[PDB]
Image (cartoon, one colour):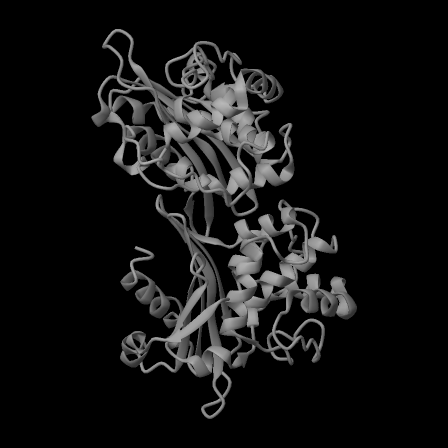
Length: 244
Length: 247
């Protein structure tokens, strides 16, 4: 069950933003959202795919363990902040595309499909190059699906060892307060055209008191200066809900 | 660890606040440690709430603690602190340093099993005498700053005599600060004010994952007044900031 919530609309209007926020308390069986339709509309996951990809890499042996260091080969990378040795969390936090491209390559097409079928991850479409399906390929996932996936990860219910799920879960911690804990991941497919904009994500969950809140946010974006919004809107909503 | 050296440049931070204490900072890659006081780095003090780390690990290994989602339910009886008077997660119980919650864990583990795991952990003098539910706060257990960093490193590398799964669960419960470039796992300790002539101890132990480097730390100080308690975080914080590790 997904229920529309009209009071969150002000945060999208003030910023003139076409997006959606899904927020589920305790479990994914009853979620609230500003837009029923968009909540289940599937977009390029981009860097949010680093979550399932981190689990898959661990399950397949490609990523050797928790303390694996992804070494830089000295060859130029698209961002300067990727041009260094990286940990799992490190690669996840700076969104180190080439690190995860190489992981994806070594997983291979067969195993990638197998695990995305297991995880019920989006349209499960990995076609159009193994190193680029989540960024420019055919893979599509919705905010509701991102939410169901993360709850499985939280509860250790994914088709993977609890060990490997815990490893990724720690790699996802972005905010630690005395009151609450935040696990989250950003995505950004690019700017695209004005007619066909890119997509920006912020997905994750919050552990406050003895309660859990699962969340996923996406929005249309044609200008990178609007990027901070992918965190500020869902944060503003969750702050006014008393969550963070 | 591999080596330790005395570094008296950190004394500035202790001198400013009239604090008698010690900081140990060890770099995982080089296996090398630095401390302002080699002598105190090896002096064994009451772990206080820092014992919650191994206690949580032992609690998860013996099955006394179910999993990472176990709620330590509050019945309704009056407790020593207002912050403890609610239902708490594993992290919550660790963060607020809930004494009754972990006493209950300790008692269900019992002396025999606690002794066994502390031997396996090499945790201080291994003296659990003075009541199963108070040996860490007012009993006979003593651990040093060098011992703590060795213990926490063993936890970090999952080398402790417990399942990796349980060591992961505790490691996340200890996360206290998260930034894009660094991650802080930490635990506070406070044994009480004692007296004017026999001061109490306050701890801050943990580790920082920064870049591909890991920094293990143990801080303690003589404390006779609760007003000086926030100094257990600020002094080592100021040290690690000046080392370029955090902030």
